[PDB]
Image (cartoon, rainbow, N blue to C red):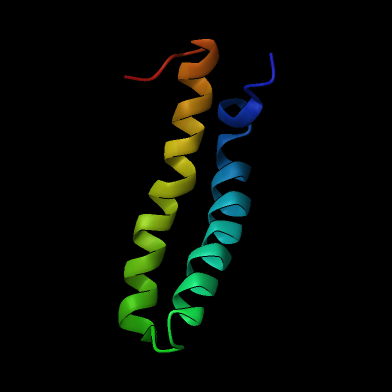
Length: 68
């Protein structure tokens, strides 16, 4: 089952949330390059949930532990 997104949870959070931080910061940089730790910390909050949401999505996808 390719839902290892839950299985590797701790490593997933570190790695995925980082790359999603990159994602969100990138878009928020191209929005006119403003962001600022205010926006960026706020970004990372949504970002950790961004990858964690997708990780919940994986678990629900197979219904490994599930997610609802």
